[PDB]
Structures are given as structure tokens and as C-alpha cells.
Image 1 (tube, helix red, strand yellow):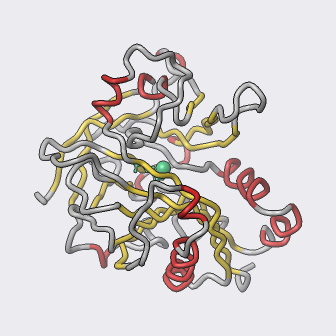
Image 2 (image 1 turned 30 degrees about the vertical axis):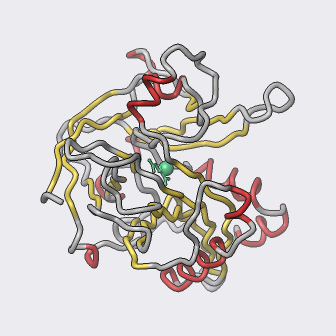
Length: 289
Ligand SMILES: O=C(O)CNC(=O)C(=O)O
Ligand SMILES: [Cu+2]
């Protein structure tokens, strides 16, 4: 709960320098993926949250309370009220006409310990549980956003809702007060279009009976400067708080469209491993053409 942190971030390593362009989600090998590392400054915004919104910067920290407390049972979450409570809040915060909550991802493993525990495991093995997303990314590219819409909605509702303004937003809530590996978000205005690279993202569920689940992300080019990209986080985020992260917005002028984000360690990290859920939401404004 210092004013800032200077931490090494993981950015896109160009293929010319040895990089690859497949993000193997949930696998051991992704933890060994190579990156272009750069030191960036992340400003603590605890107390300054009112100066950040999804329209300008693409992200927002909100006070939102929920009755749900246990998050590691995927089935119990999907069949409980959590998705509906996220919907009501997001609809209220965004003024959306309709909110579709598609799913969530639970993270609870410590990054370093998992690297150690899995150092002899084959690349394509899938960890039991999920570690922090410790690299700069946007969960959906522009192409990936369209791909998700038609994968997560019926074909005709996806075609109807594509005719009005729609957006993808992750709602990130910790299981408890964050005392290690917080979540950094990057001002959408401070990253140019030509720094974004459509990067394919695969999860080999049910292999070999099924092709790995397909997704397309933004990878982000490294900055020349610690402050070229404008990074922010909020220290001590509690389970009563939600970090909204706009991955995509169909509206090209007048609103932020994509937020690079990444978990990061601080030297003041302590306590049992950070646990969180990020719930993926489609947001629609059927008023807006
Ligand atoms: O929590 C983490 O470590 C990473 N989370 C995300 O990237 C997200 O919510 O989209
Ligand atoms: Cu993410």
C-alpha cells in the first residue's frame, strides 16, 4: 500500500527473437513461455478509484457485495446466484440493456511454487488449478471477440446483438483481501493499435477426443519506457470489491476498446496464495446502433 511499484512485466517477444504465438492456457508449458521483459511502473490507485472508468480508461474498481463465499467449486458457482448478482451490478454500472454472464475462471495457485512443483512435468500437462496470469494480454482481440460471441451465444442472438453496441468485460474479485500477486490494468489510451498482435489461445480440454478450445487474444508489444504504458492497480482489494476490465467494445470512436492487464508480484507479497474469480460477461446496449 505504497504509492507505486516498479516491477518487471512480461511483454510480447517477436518471433524473430525466438517467440511463439500460441498461448497454451492452463498448461505447464505456458509457465515456461518466453517473453520480452520490461520494467514498468504501476501506480497504486487505492483512494483514487473515482478517477477511472470503463469509457475513458477501460477499467473500473467498484464496491459490490455478494452473498457467495466459496468459489473453487465450478458447479456450485454456475448453479448459484453469483452470475445473476454480477449481471445486476454490471448492468447498473454500464447502463447496459442486457448482460450475458458466460462463465468464470478460478485462480488460487502460487506462481513460483507451481513452477517448482511442475519443473519435471511435460509441457502439455494441465495444472490442477490455475496460477496468476503473469503476462500482459487482452483476453479477446477484435477477431477473438466476434469468435466468442458466436461460440457463447446462439447463432441468431449473436447476429441480432451484433447490430447494436456490445462489449466484453471480465469482473475480477478476490476470494479475500489481496496480500500477494495483485492485478495490474493498463490505460487503453496509452497503448497504440500497432502494439497489439492477434495471438491464438488454446486449452487442450478432453484431448485427444476434442480439438483444443479456441480463443484469440491480444499480445502487447514491449514499451521503450517504464511509464510509456500507464499501469494501475488497487492495493488491498477485498471480496467486497470487483475490478471491471473491458476486453472489447464494438464502438470504435469515443470509448476505450481494450485493456492490457497482467498479474504481478510485489516484494511485499505475503500470505497464503491469492485466490480470485474472473467472470466473463457480454454487455449489450440495444439502444445504441
Ligand atoms: O488474476 C489473474 O492473475 C489474471 N486474471 C485475468 O487476466 C483476467 O481477469 O482476465
Ligand atoms: Cu485476463
